Structure formats: C-alpha cells, structure tokens
Length: 312
Ligand SMILES: Oc1ccc(F)cc1Nc1nc(-c2ccncc2)cs1
Image (cartoon, rainbow, N blue to C red; front, side, top):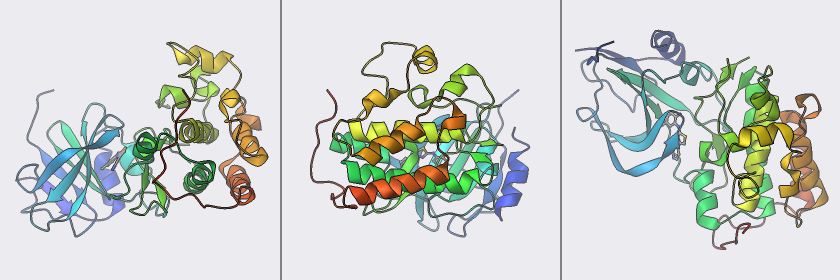
C-alpha cells in the first residue's frame, strides 16, 4: 500500500516540497489527469504502468521514455529522476500555469529513491531531433519556432519564472510541426540558479552574477544558432572549457549565417547582448522575430523533406 491519489496541481506541489539514507518502496504522488489512474492508492512501475520502445531523449537529471498506463492504455512521457537530484522547481514552477507554448504535466509519483514525472507526449518529437534529422532548419522555420519559444518565455517571465535551460532538446513539436512548446523545468527558478547546457549559457551565469529572465533570452538565441547552423554555438571554434570563452569572447554573433536577412541578424544580435541590461526581453524579441519572419516572406518551408547541410 501507499499514498498515490488523483488531484490538482497545488496538491502535487505541496507534496513535492517534502521530497526536497536507506532505499524504500514508498509509493506516493498525485496524478493530474483521469487518464492516469492509481490502483488502491498505488502507482508502481511494471505493475500499473510500463515504459516501452527506445528512449525519447535526455531530460534534465534523468532519461525520458514513452510510457503506458496498463489499465487505461493511455500513452505519455515519463522522466525518471533519482530523488537526490530531483529539483522541486520542476513541479512547482508550472502549478496553475497553462499555455499552448508549455507542455502540460500529468503528475509525478515517487517510488523509493525515484521520482517519475509524467508529461504529455507530442508526436512531432523534439526540436533537437528535428535538427539532427534535417541537418539544420531554413531561416523562416527557425524564426517561426523561436517566435513560439519566445511566446512561452513571455508567459513565464511575466510570472517571474526562469525556464533555465531553453534549448532545442527541451522544445517539443506537434504531429504536423506547426506547434512548438517548452518542456522540462528541471533548471527552472522562481525569481540559487543551477546552470544549464554550457553552450547555451549567458555570460552573467558563468560570471556568477544575479540571474534574471534575460538568461532565457540568451539561451533561446543560442538555440536559434543551433537551428540555423546545425550545431551548438562555440563548439566549432573552441576546444574545451567554454565557460571562460563565453565570459571573455565577443558574443557569438559571428555564427549568424551570412544568408540571414537584416532583421533576423538584428534580432539574434539583440538576444545575444553580453550585458543583460542591453539584452532584449521576451516581449521585445518576440515582436522583432515576428517582423523578421514577415520580411523573409512568412513561413513557407515544409517542416521536413529537404536535408540542408549544416556548418562544416
Ligand atoms: O522534465 C520532464 C518531465 C516529464 C517528462 F515526461 C519529460 C521531461 N523532460 C523532457 N522531455 C523531453 C522529451 C519528451 C518527449 N519527447 C522528446 C523529448 C525532453 S526533456
């Protein structure tokens, strides 16, 4: 027996707060959708639910899988995280939030030293998977996705929530690739910041200065460069510890493809100002990116079909 129940977001957050020696079989948590059903107040892997197929990808602090509720047959995603590296922020930051640009959480359930976080599965795959498959993305589609990402950031930032690791691997697409949404709040902060992916990290992060929402903007423009070039910024120019190069080198605007139109290059420049004070906000950048997309003639490229050679 255990303490897994059906309820709302706030009841999950409250319990998650208590998660922060020996290894137990303690089973407890909150399922947020009727599609995931506790059985006699239990929800245990291999008994009531199971993972299958290959991994979906890497999440913060744990692996992500396809899973199925054995009773309802309902399919979703699960990130399994060891209790000692589980951050509460992942289940508190988005409680009471709802946006088309944010992948909804289905709940979380602890099973001894493991915390299983359940989330909607979008069948388009991740933006990171799109890049790998296609080499890189054309300018219009990259702008379109950045726009959508930035809309997600507006929604977060006005609530003083920092996503903390905005990157293609944490953006999910819909089945026709027309919709992108943010996921994985493992590094989220409610405005001590646990830094995300090194290649996407702002100078103020490596400098150890107080971080604000502008960290997400920098990261999102690093993601933009990744979509355009097919690789994370820095990696094609620099060898090892990117920490110091982010802090000391000019911002990676040299990595903007020469083919990009004026306003595309401008937006990326403004999203990549070294001093957060001069860096564009999500509201500002979203507007510029919107103008930028119009000026290249709107979204025209099909989401797949043409492999584009990345930067050598
Ligand atoms: O923080 C989480 C909480 C619950 C989850 F089920 C997943 C995540 N994290 C991530 N999921 C993905 C992903 C999902 C589905 N397909 C491709 C990638 C990338 S990072």
